[PDB]
C-alpha cells in the first residue's frame, strides 16, 4: 500500500491469504524493536554482504524489485536469525540488560553505555564480532567509546570502562 | 546603396533636423564641427552594420543549404 | 561638527562608535561573519582540525558488481 | 581510466569553437585571461565614471556642493562592477567555445593532462556533497551568458563540465608511454 | 485509500519545513532571488508613495 | 520542428539524494549514451570544420 | 548587472534625502543600463532554441538576448527625459569645442530650466524603472510557472508604483489605484491558470508541459484538455496587461490620469516583455496534427482579441478629444495587428511579429517625446482660451487636449512634421516604416488563410486613419491660439550671461532674451533619429529584417 | 471542491460590488487563498514538496500586494477624504 | 515530477516521469516523426500515478463483485475484532487458528 503518512485512518485491513507454495517459506525475525538495536551492530558485522547484496539486487532491477529479489531477502533474514540465535546462546544476560535499558531510555544508545560495553565484551569473546561505526573522525575518541557522554541523562560511573578489543 | 555613404548622410540629416526642431540656425561657423562629428558617427555605425551584414549572409547561406539537405535526405529515405 | 566619512575615514569611525554605537557595531558584527568565513577555516586546516565526514542520510550502497554470495540458502532454513 | 568519462547528461550548444568547460572554476577563468582581457575590462570600467564626468561638463546638473562627488563614487563602483564582469565574461567565453580559443585549448590540454599523470582529481576536490556538487554545476553551467541580468560565479570543485574527459587520459597515456621509452633507451 | 510502512525511505525522515529548506536555498534558489526583490520593491515603493520626506 | 530538445537535459540528474528506496531510480544509461553521442558528434563537426578550413 | 545596479543605487539613495541629487541618479541609471547592453551583446555567440540556466528555472535564447538589449535601449531613451533639463540657453559665442569643453557659462538657470520641477525631484524614480526593467527581462527568460508568476508580479507591482509616484496629484493616485485593482484581478487569472497546469501535469517546467502536449498531439483515460483550458485562462490575464479588447477599458483612463513622463514608460515596456513571452508559448503549443486538441486551441482567444481590438481601437477613437486617451486607443488597434501575427503561427507571421513589435515600440516612443517637447516649448507662449484654464495637473500633463495643438506648424514647423511623419506611420502610409509592418502582417495572414481578418484589418485601418488625420488637420489646417509671451521680448527685458574661462575669469558678458532659449539637445536629437528611421527605412532595411529572418529560422529550425 | 467554491466567493465579491473598493481588495485575497489552497491539496496527493514551496511564494507575493494596495489606497485617501464611489 | 517528496526523500511519480522523459528523448527526433508514439503508454502511466483514475475504476468494480459475493454466501462464525487483534501473538494460538480456519 502507498507510503504516504495517514491522517484520518480509523480501520486496519488484514489479508489472511497465505504466500503461494511456489515461493520457499522463511521463518520470520521475532525480536522486537529494542532487541534489534542492541544486536544491530553485530548483524552488520556478519550480514553486511547479504544486506548489501539484497539492496543491490533491488537497485539492479528498478520497479520490479519486491519480486525478482525474493531469494536475497530470505538470505538476509537467515543471517540475522543466526546473530539473534548466537547472542541468546552466549550473552543472554548482557543482551537483555542492554535492550531493557534502551526500552526506558528512548532507545537512545548513549543512554546505556555501561550495559552496551559489557555486551560488546561478551559478544567479542564468544562470537568474535565487533561494533564498528564507519567513517568516524580521526582526531578524537570514538563517541561509542567515550568515558563521558554529554547527552546522557544519567552520568556514566568512572569504574564502568569502555570495551576496547584488546588491552 | 552604399552603407557607409547612407549612414554618413543619415548623421548629417540628423544634425539638420535637430537644428530645425530647435529652430536654431543651420551653418553658424563656431558650431560647424557638429556636422563632421554627426557624419563620423554615421560612418562608424555602418562599418558596424557591414560586419552585421557579412555574418547574417553566412548564416542565411548555411540555413538555405540545411533546408536543402532536410528536403533532400527525406526524399532519399522515401525512395524505398 | 560631526565628521564626514569620505574626508576623514578614521575620524568618522571613532565618532560613529561613540555617537551611533548600535548602528556602528551592527556593521562591525555583520562584517565579522564574512571575516570568520575567510579566516578560521584555513587556520583550522593548518592546526589539523579536519571537518567530520557527512553522516549517511540514505542507505549506503557500495559501488561495483554484486559479490556473488554463497550461504544462508533455502536448504539451510 | 575511470571507465566513464561522460557521467552526466549535458546540454550541447551549437558554437563555432571547441568547448573546454561548461563551468570553469573562477581561478581558471582568471588564470586563462589574455592581456587584452585586462585592457578591455579597464577600458569599460573607466567609461561609466568618464561618461558621467563628460555629461556634467557638457550639460551641467546644477546640483549642490557635494552631490557630484557622491555620484562619482556610485558611477565608479558600477564601472568596477561592469568592468570586471566584462573582463570575466570575455575570458570565460573561450571556455564555452563562443570565442576563438586555440590558445586556451592547449593550456587546458596541458594542465588537465599534467593533473592526470599527477594522480590529481581532474577538476579538484569538493568539500560539498556529490549531490550539492551537482546542484552547483547545474546553476553555473553557461551562466556568464546571463551576466547582464544576474551575476553568478563557480567556486565549487565539481566534476560535471560537459566534456568527455577520455582525451586528457588518452593523452596522458600516450605521454607516459613516450617518456618510458626514453628512460629505457638511456 | 490504503497505506503501508517502508523502511529504506524512513531512515532519516524530515519534517515538511526541513524538506522545503533542503531545496529552497540551493536547487530553486532563483525563486528566492525574485522574491527577495519583490519584497524589497514593496518596501521602497510603499514608503516612497506615502511619507513626506524629512 | 515537431520534436522538442530539452533546454535543460540536466533534469535527468534531478531527484532527492536522501531516504532513497532501493530500485526507486531508473536505469538511465541509455539516456547518457544519447547525450554522449551528441557531444562527440558536435565536437567532430567543429573539429572537421576549423581544421579542414584552416589549411 | 541590473541587479548589481539596483543594490548600489538603492544603497546610495538610502543614505541621502537631497532632491537636487535626482538628476545625477538618473544619469547613472543610463550608464548602468549601458553596461547591461555590453554584457547581453557579448552573450550572442551561439545557436540554440534555448539553454536552461540556474537549475532550469531560467532559459537563454538568441531571441531572449536581442529583446533584453532592445528593452535596455528603450529604457535608456525614456531615462533621458529625467536626466537632462527640458530647455537650454545657446549663443553662437559659446558653441565651439574650446567653449563647451574648457570655457563655462553662468546665468540664473532656475526658471529657464525648471530646475525644481516635479520630474526633477523624485529620487527613487530611476530605481523604480530599474525594478520594472528587471521583471521584464526576467519574464522573457522564464522556464518555470513559478518564475513566470514571480516575474510578472515584479513587473506589475513596479508599474503600479510608477503610476502613484506623483503623490500630490489627485489624478495620478486615482490612476495607480485603478491600475492596481484591475491589475490584481488580472494576476489572479494568471495564477489560476498556472495552478491548474501543475495540478494536472505534476510539473512546473514549461519543457515538460511542451512534451506532454507533444505526445498528446497524435491523430484514452487521460485526455490533455487542461493544457488548452489552462492557457486560455492564463492568456486572459496577459491580455488585460497588454490592454487588448475586451479587457481594455482600464488603459485610456490610467494613461490619461498619470503624468506624461510616466506614460511613456508604462505604455511601452509591459507590452514588449509580455508579447515576446507569448510567442514561445504559441510555438510549442501548436497542433501539427489536426485532432480534437486543435479545436480548443487557446490561440482562438488571441484571434478574437485581435478582431475586437481592431474594431474597438479604431472605432472608439473617433470621438476622443483628449490626446492621451487618443493615443491609448491607438495602441489598442496596434495590438490587434500584433495579436493577429502571433495567432497565425507561421515562419512569415513570426518575422512580421518581430518587426511590428520593435518598430511600434520605437515609433510610439517618438509620439511620446514629441508630445512632452511641445509641452515644454509653450513656456515662452501664453494663451487666453477659456478651456485651457480649467485643465487639471497642467504641470504633469502640459498637453491634454488635441485643440491645444492647433496651429503648432506656425510655432514649430519641423516638430510638427516629426509628429506628422510619426502619425502617418501609425496610419500605415508608404514609404513610412509602419507601412512595411502592416504589409508583412497582412501577407502572413493572407498566405496562411486569414483573408477574412485581413479585410477587417484594412477596413479598420481606414477608420483608425480618421482620428489620426484629425490630429494632423488640427496642427496644420488652423492658426494657433497660443501667442508669444510679450514680456520675454520687451526690449528692456534681458538676462545677463557671463562667459568665463578655465580659471574663472570673465571672457565675455552677453545680453540674452527669450529668443535665446531652446529645447535641450537630448530631446531634439532623439526625435530626429527616430523620425529619420521612419522616413528612411526603405534605404536601410537589410540588417533589421535579416535579424528577424535568422531569429525565426532558429525557433522553427529542425 | 472547497477550493472552487472559495474561488467563486472571490468572484462573487466582484459581482456584488458597486461601492466597496475595500471588498475589491478583499476578494482578490480570497481568490489567492483558493489557488494556494488548491495547489497545496494536490501537492499532498502527489507527494511533492514543490507544491508546498509554490504556495509559500504565493503567500509572500500576496502580502506584498496588500502593502502596495493599502499603500496606494492611503495615497488616494489623503487627497480624496473618501473611499466611496459616487453612483 | 520534481523529484523531492514530503519526507525528505524522492517524489512517488518521479520514476514514471523519467521513464517518460527517457522514452521521448531517445526515440523521437526530427528524422522520425512517429518515434514519440512509443511515449503514449509511458505517458499514460505517468498520468495514472498522479491521478489514479484507472486503479480507482478497477478497485470500484472488484469491490462491487466481492461485496455481493460475500453477501449471499453462508457465514459460519465471523471472527470478532478482539480475536483478530490477538492474531500471531505468542500466547493466543487458539485465536489464530480460528482466524485462519486451519
Ligand atoms: C542576485 C545577486 C547575486 C550576487 C552575488 C553573486 C554570487 C555568485 C555565486 C557565489 C555564491 C556561491 C558560491 C559559494 C558556495 C559554496 O559552496 O562555495 C564553495 C566553497 C568551497 O567549495 P569547494 O567544493 O571546495 O570548491 C573549491 C573552492 O573554491 C576552494 O575553497 P577555498 O579553500 O578557497 O575556501 C576559502 C574561501 C571560501 O570562498 C569560496 O571558496 C567561495 C566564496 C567566494 C565568494 C566571493 C564573493 C562573490 C563574488 O574563502 C576565501 O577565499 C575568502 C572569501 C570568504 C567569504 C568572504 C565574504 C564574501 C562576501 C563579501 C560581501 O565553500 C566554502 O568555502 C564555504 C564558504 C562560502 C561562503 C560564500 C558566501 C557568499 C555570500 C555572498 C553575499 C552577497
Ligand atoms: C548590507 C548593507 C549595509 C549598509 C550600511 C553600510 C554603512 C552605511 O550606511 O554607510 C554610509 C555611512 C554614512 O556616511 P556619510 O558620509 O554620512 O554619508 C553621506 C555621504 O555622501 C556618503 O555617500 P556615498 O554614496 O558616497 O556613500 C554611501 C555608500 C557608498 O556608496 C558608494 O560610494 C557606491 C555604492 C556602493 C554599493 C555597494 C553595493 C554592494 O556607503 C555604503 O553603503 C558602502 C557599503 C559597502 O558611512 C559611509 O559612507 C561608509 C562607507 C563605507
Ligand atoms: C539607427 C540610428 C543610427 C544613428 C547613426 C548616427 C546618427 C547621428 C548621431 C549623432 C550623435 C551625436 C552625439 C553627440 C552630440 O550630441 O553632439 C552634439 C553635442 C552638443 O552640441 P549642441 O547640440 O550644439 O548643444 C549645445 C550645448 O552642448 C547644449 O546641449 P545640452 O546641454 O542641451 O545637451 C548636450 C548633450 C547632453 O549629453 C551629453 O552631455 C553627452 C554625454 C555623452 C557621454 O546632448 C547630447 O549630446 C545629446 C545626445 C543624444 C544622443 C542619443 C539620442 C538617442 O556636442 C558636444 O559638445 C558634445 C561633446 C561631443 C560628443 C561626445 C559624446 C559622443 C557620443 C555620445 C553618445 C550618446
Ligand atoms: C531609430 C531609433 C534609434 C533609437 C536610438 C538607438 C539606435 C540604435 C538601435 C539599436 C541598434 C543596435 C544596438 C545594439 C547595442 C550596441 C552594439 C553596437 O553597435 O556595437 C556593439 C559593440 C560591442 O563591442 P565589444 O568590444 O564588446 O565587441 C567585441 C568584438 N569585436 C572586437 C570583434 C567587435 O559595442 C558595445 O560595447 C556594446 C554596448 C555599447 C553601449 C550601449 C549602446 C546602446 C545603443
Ligand atoms: C566603514 C565605517 C562604518 C560604516 C558606517 C557605520 C554607521 C555609522 C552610523 C550611520 C549614520 O551616521 C550618521 O548618523 C547621523 C544620524 O543623526 C546622521 O548625521 C547627520 O545626519 C544629517 C545629515 O543627513 C544631519 O542633519 C545631522 O546634523 C547629522 O547628525 C547621518 O545619518 C550619518 O552621518
Ligand atoms: C532596431 C533593432 C534593435 C535591435 C536591438 C538588438 C541589437 C543587437 C545587436 C548586437 C548583436 C550582436 O553583435 C555582436 O556583438 C559581439 C560583442 O562581443 C561581437 O561578436 C563577437 O563576439 C566574440 C567576441 O566577443 C567573437 O568571438 C565573435 O566571433 C564575434 O561575433 C560583435 O560586435 C557582434 O557580432
Ligand atoms: C535601424 C536598424 C539597424 C539594424 C539593427 C539590427 C542590427 C543587429 C542585428 C544583429 C543580429 C543578427 O546578426 C547575427 O545574429 C546571430 C544570431 O543571433 C549572431 O551570430 C553570433 O552567433 C554565431 C553562432 O555561434 C557566432 O559564431 C557569431 O560569431 C555571432 O556573431 C549575432 O547576433 C549576429 O552575428
Ligand atoms: C471582393 C473584395 C476583394 C476580395 C479579394 C481581395 C484580394 C484577394 C487576393 C486573391 O485572393 C487570395 O487568393 C490566394 C490564392 O488563391 C489565397 O492564398 C492562399 O494561400 C494558400 C497557399 O497554400 C492557399 O492554400 C489558401 O487557400 C490561401 O490562403 C489568399 O488567401 C487570397 O486572399
Image (spheres, coloured by chain):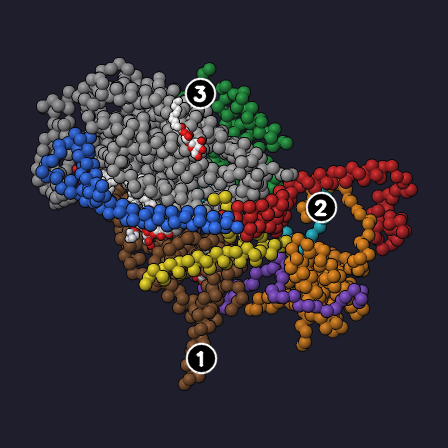
Chain colours: A orange, B blue, C purple, D brown, E cyan, F yellow, H green, I red
For disc 3, the chain is H
Task: Please give the name of the residue rendered at 29% of the width and 46% of the height, measured from the top-left corner.
Answer: B53
Task: Name the residue: 10% across, 31% down.
Answer: G511
Q: Are marks 3 and 1 in contact (CB under 8 Å)?
A: no
Measure the alpha-carbon separation of dots 3 and 1. 93 Å
Whether residue G22 is situated above or below residue E21 in the rendered picture: above
Instruction: Find the residue positioned furthest to the right.
Output: I76
| Front position in the image: B3 or B29 | B3
Mark 1 vs mark 2: give the one in front.
Answer: 1
Q: Is residue G95 visible?
A: yes
- Residue at numbered disc 1: D180
Left or right: G38 as drawn, with respect to F43 = left
Question: How many C-alpha atoms fall within 10 Å of the one at disc 3: few (<14), some, or many (≥20)?
Answer: few
Which numbered tag is attached to residue H82?
3
User: Where in the image, quadrant-wise, is ligand 3 located?
Assistant: top left
Which x, y percent locates residue G347?
A: 41, 39
Please state which of residues G193 and H38 is positioned toward the viewer in this rendering.
G193
Q: Decide: few, some or many residues near mark 2? Use Cα within 10 Å; few <14, some 14-19, many ≥20.
A: some
- Provide the chain ID for the residue under circle 2: E
Q: Quadrant of residue H80?
A: top left
Residue that protrudes farthest toward the bottom in the picture? D186
Image marks 2 and 3: residues in contact by CB distance under 8 Å: no
Task: Say if G363 sits above or below A18 in the image.
Answer: above
Find residue E3 and name its label: 2
- What residue do we see at 15% from left, 27% from top? G514
Q: Tell which subunit mark 1 falls on.
A: D
Amino acid at each position: 500500500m502507498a507510503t504516504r503518512k495517514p491522517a484520518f485512518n480509523q480501520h486496519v485491513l488484514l489479508d489472511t491469504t497465505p504466500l503461494p507454495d511456489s515461493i520457499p517459506k522463511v521463518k520470520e525475525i521475532g525480536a522486537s524493536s529494542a532487541p534489534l538495536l542492541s544486536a544491530s551492530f553485530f548483524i552488520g558485522a556478519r550480514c553486511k554482504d547479504y544486506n548489501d547484496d539484497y539492496m543491490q539486487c533491488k537497485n539492479e532491477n528498478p520497479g520490479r524489485g519486491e519480486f525478482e529479489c525474493l531469494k536475497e531477502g530470505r538470505r538476509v533474514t537467515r543471517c540475522a536469525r543466526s546473530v539473534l540465535k548466537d547472542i541468546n546462546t552466549h550473552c543472554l544476560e548482557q543482551f537483555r540488560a542492554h535492550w531493557q535499558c534502551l526500552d526506558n531510555n528512548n532507545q537512545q544508545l548513549w543512554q546505556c553505555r555501561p550495559a552496551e560495553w559489557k555486551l560488546n565484551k561478551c559478544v567479542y569473546e564468544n562470537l568474535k564480532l565487533e561494533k564498528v561505526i564507519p567513517d568516524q573522525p580521526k582526531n578524537s575518541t570514538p563517541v561509542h567509546l567515550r568515558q563521558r557522554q554529554i547527552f546522557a541523562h544519567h552520568a556514566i560511573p568512572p569504574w564502568e570502562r569502555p570495551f576496547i578489543p584488546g588491552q | 546603396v552604399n552603407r557607409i555613404l547612407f549612414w554618413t548622410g543619415f548623421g548629417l540629416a540628423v544634425r539638420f533636423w535637430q537644428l530645425g526642431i530647435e529652430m536654431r540656425p543651420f551653418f553658424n561657423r563656431k558650431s560647424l564641427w557638429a556636422y563632421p562629428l554627426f557624419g563620423g558617427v554615421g560612418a562608424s555605425f555602418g562599418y558596424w552594420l557591414q560586419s552585421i551584414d557579412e555574418k547574417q549572409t553566412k548564416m542565411l547561406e548555411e540555413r538555405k543549404q540545411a533546408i536543402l539537405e532536410k528536403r533532400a535526405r527525406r526524399a532519399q529515405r522515401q525512395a524505398e | 561638527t560631526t565628521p564626514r566619512f569620505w574626508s576623514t575615514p578614521l575620524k568618522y569611525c571613532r565618532w560613529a562608535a561613540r555617537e551611533r554605537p548600535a548602528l556602528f557595531f551592527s556593521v562591525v558584527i555583520g562584517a565579522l561573519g564574512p571575516v570568520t568565513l575567510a579566516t578560521v577555516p584555513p587556520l583550522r586546516r593548518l592546526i589539523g582540525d579536519v571537518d567530520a565526514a557527512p553522516i549517511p542520510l540514505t542507505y549506503p550502497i557500495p559501488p561495483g558488481p554484486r559479490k556473488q554470495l554463497k550461504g544462508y540458502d533455502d536448504d539451510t532454513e | 581510466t575511470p571507465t566513464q568519462t561522460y557521467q552526466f547528461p549535458s546540454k550541447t550548444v551549437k558554437t563555432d569553437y571547441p568547448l573546454i568547460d561548461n563551468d570553469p572554476h573562477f581561478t581558471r577563468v582568471i588564470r586563462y585571461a589574455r592581456p587584452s582581457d585586462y585592457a578591455h575590462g579597464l577600458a569599460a570600467a573607466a567609461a561609466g565614471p568618464a561618461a558621467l564626468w563628460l555629461m556634467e561638463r557638457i550639460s551641467p546638473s546644477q546640483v549642490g556642493r557635494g552631490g557630484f562627488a557622491k555620484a562619482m563614487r556610485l558611477a565608479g563602483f558600477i564601472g568596477l562592477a561592469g568592468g570586471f564582469l566584462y573582463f570575466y565574461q570575455r575570458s570565460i567565453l573561450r571556455f564555452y567555445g563562443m570565442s576563438e580559443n586555440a590558445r586556451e585549448v592547449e593550456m587546458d590540454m596541458r594542465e588537465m593532462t599534467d593533473r592526470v599523470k599527477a594522480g590529481l582529481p581532474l577538476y579538484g576536490e569538493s568539500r560539498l556533497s556529490p549531490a550539492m556538487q551537482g546542484v552547483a554545476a547545474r546553476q553555473s553551467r553557461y551562466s556568464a551568458l546571463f551576466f547582464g541580468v544576474m551575476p553568478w560565479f563557480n567556486f565549487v570543485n565539481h566534476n560535471q563540465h560537459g566534456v568527455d574527459t577520455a582525451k586528457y587520459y588518452q593523452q596522458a597515456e600516450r605521454e607516459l608511454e613516450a617518456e618510458r621509452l626514453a628512460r629505457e633507451q638511456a | 485509500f490504503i497505506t503501508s510502512k517502508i523502511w529504506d525511505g524512513a531512515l532519516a525522515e524530515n519534517n515538511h519545513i526541513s524538506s522545503i529548506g533542503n531545496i529552497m536555498y540551493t536547487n530553486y534558489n532563483v525563486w528566492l532571488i525574485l522574491a527577495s526583490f519583490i519584497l524589497l520593491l514593496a518596501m521602497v515603493g510603499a514608503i516612497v508613495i506615502t511619507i513626506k520626506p524629512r | 520542428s515537431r520534436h522538442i530538445e530539452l533546454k535543460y537535459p540536466e533534469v535527468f540528474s534531478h531527484g532527492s539524494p536522501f531516504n532513497v528506496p532501493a530500485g526507486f531510480y531508473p536505469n538511465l544509461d541509455h539516456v547518457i549514451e544519447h547525450y554522449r553521442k551528441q557531444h562527440l558528434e558536435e565536437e567532430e563537426r567543429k573539429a572537421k570544420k576549423l581544421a579542414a578550413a584552416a589549411a | 548587472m541590473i541587479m548589481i545596479s539596483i543594490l548600489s543605487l538603492l544603497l546610495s539613495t538610502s543614505v541621502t534625502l537631497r532632491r537636487d541629487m535626482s538628476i545625477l541618479f538618473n544619469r547613472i541609471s543610463i550608464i548602468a543600463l549601458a553596461y547591461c547592453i555590453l554584457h547581453d551583446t557579448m552573450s550572442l555567440s551561439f545557436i540554440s532554441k534555448g539553454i536552461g540556466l540556474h537549475g532550469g528555472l531560467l532559459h537563454i535564447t538568441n531571441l531572449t538576448q536581442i529583446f533584453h538589449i532592445f528593452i535596455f535601449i528603450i529604457s535608456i531613451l525614456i531615462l533621458q527625459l529625467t536626466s537632462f533639463y527640458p530647455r537650454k540657453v545657446w549663443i553662437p559665442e559659446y558653441s565651439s569645442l574650446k567653449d563647451i569643453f574648457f570655457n563655462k557659462i553662468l546665468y540664473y538657470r532656475t526658471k529657464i530650466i525648471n530646475k525644481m520641477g516635479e520630474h526633477m525631484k523624485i529620487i527613487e524614480y530611476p530605481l523604480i524603472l530599474l525594478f520594472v526593467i528587471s521583471g521584464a527581462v526576467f519574464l522573457i527568460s522564464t522556464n518555470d510557472l513559478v518564475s513566470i508568476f514571480l516575474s510578472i508580479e515584479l513587473q506589475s507591482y513596479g508599474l503600479y508604483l510608477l503610476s502613484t509616484i506623483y503623490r500630490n496629484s489627485e489624478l495620478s493616485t486615482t490612476g495607480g489605484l485603478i491600475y492596481f485593482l484591475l491589475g490584481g484581478l488580472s494576476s489572479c487569472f494568471i495564477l489560476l491558470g498556472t495552478s491548474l497546469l501543475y495540478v494536472n501535469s505534476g510539473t512546473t517546467s514549461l519543457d515538460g508541459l511542451y512534451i506532454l502536449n507533444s505526445i498528446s498531439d497524435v491523430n484514452s483515460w487521460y485526455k490533455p484538455y487542461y493544457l488548452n483550458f489552462s492557457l486560455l485562462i492564463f492568456s486572459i490575464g496577459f491580455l488585460f496587461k497588454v490592454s487588448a479588447a475586451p479587457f481594455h477599458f482600464w488603459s485610456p483612463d490610467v494613461y490619461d490620469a498619470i503624468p506624461t513622463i510616466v506614460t511613456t514608460f508604462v505604455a511601452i515596456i509591459a507590452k514588449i516583455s509580455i508579447f515576446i513571452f507569448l510567442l514561445e508559448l504559441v510555438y510549442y503549443t501548436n497542433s501539427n496534427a489536426n485532432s480534437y486538441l486543435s479545436e480548443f486551441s487557446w490561440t482562438y482567444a488571441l484571434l478574437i482579441s485581435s478582431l475586437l481590438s481592431l474594431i474597438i481601437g479604431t472605432v472608439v477613437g473617433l470621438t476622443q478629444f483628449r490626446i492621451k486617451r487618443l493615443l491609448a486607443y491607438s495602441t489598442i488597434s496596434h495590438v490587434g495587428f500584433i495579436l493577429l501575427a502571433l495567432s497565425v503561427s507561421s515562419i512569415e507571421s513570426t518575422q512580421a511579429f518581430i518587426f511590428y513589435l520593435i518598430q511600434y515600440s520605437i515609433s510610439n516612443l517618438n509620439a511620446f517625446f514629441i508630445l512632452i517637447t511641445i509641452g515644454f516649448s509653450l513656456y515662452g507662449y501664453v494663451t487666453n482660451n477659456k478651456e485651457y484654464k480649467s485643465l487639471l495637473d497642467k504641470n504633469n500633463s502640459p498637453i491634454q487636449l488635441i485643440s491645444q495643438l492647433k496651429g503648432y506648424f506656425y510655432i514649430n514647423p519641423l516638430l510638427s512634421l516629426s509628429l506628422a511623419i510619426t502619425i502617418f506611420s501609425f496610419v500605415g502610409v508608404p514609404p513610412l516604416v509602419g507601412f512595411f509592418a502592416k504589409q508583412m502582417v497582412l501577407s502572413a495572414a493572407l498566405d496562411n488563410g486569414y483573408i477574412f481578418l485581413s479585410l477587417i484589418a484594412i477596413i479598420t485601418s481606414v477608420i483608425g486613419a480618421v482620428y489620426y488625420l484629425n490630429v494632423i488637420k488640427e496642427i496644420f489646417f488652423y492658426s494657433p491660439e497660443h501667442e508669444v509671451n510679450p514680456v520675454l521680448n520687451e526690449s528692456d527685458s534681458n538676462f545677463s550671461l557671463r562667459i568665463l574661462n578655465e580659471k574663472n575669469v570673465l571672457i565675455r558678458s552677453v545680453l540674452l532674451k527669450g529668443r535665446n532659449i531652446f529645447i535641450s539637445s537630448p530631446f531634439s536629437i532623439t526625435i530626429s533619429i527616430i523620425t529619420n528611421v521612419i522616413l528612411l527605412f526603405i534605404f536601410m532595411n537589410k540588417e533589421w529584417l535579416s535579424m528577424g529572418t535568422i531569429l525565426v529560422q532558429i525557433l522553427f529550425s529542425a | 471542491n472547497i477550493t472552487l467554491i472559495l474561488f467563486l466567493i472571490g468572484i462573487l465579491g466582484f459581482v456584488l460590488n458597486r461601492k466597496n473598493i475595500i471588498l475589491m481588495l478583499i476578494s482578490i485575497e480570497i481568490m489567492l487563498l483558493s489557488i494556494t489552497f488548491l495547489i497545496l491539496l494536490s501537492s499532498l496527493n502527489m507527494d511533492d514538496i514543490i507544491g508546498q514551496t509554490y504556495a509559500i511564494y504565493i503567500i509572500v507575493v500576496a502580502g506584498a500586494e496588500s502593502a502596495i494596495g493599502l499603500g496606494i489606497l492611503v495615497a488616494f485617501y489623503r487627497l480624496r477624504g473618501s473611499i466611496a464611489i459616487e453612483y | 515530477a520534481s523529484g523531492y517528496g514530503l519526507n525528505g526523500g524522492p517524489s512517488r511519480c518521479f520514476p514514471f516521469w523519467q521513464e517518460l522523459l527517457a522514452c521521448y528523448v531517445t526515440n523521437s527526433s526530427e528524422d522520425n516523426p512517429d518515434g514519440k508514439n512509443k511515449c503514449i503508454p509511458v505517458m499514460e502511466d505517468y498520468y495514472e500515478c498522479l491521478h489514479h483514475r484507472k486503479e480507482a475504476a478497477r478497485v470500484r468494480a472488484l469491490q462491487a463483485a466481492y461485496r455481493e459475493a460475500e453477501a449471499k454466501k453462508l457465514q459460519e462464525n465471523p471472527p470478532t475484532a478482539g480475536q483478530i487483534r490477538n492474531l500471531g501473538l505468542l500466547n493466543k494460538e487458539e485465536d489464530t487458528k480460528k482466524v485462519h480456519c486451519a
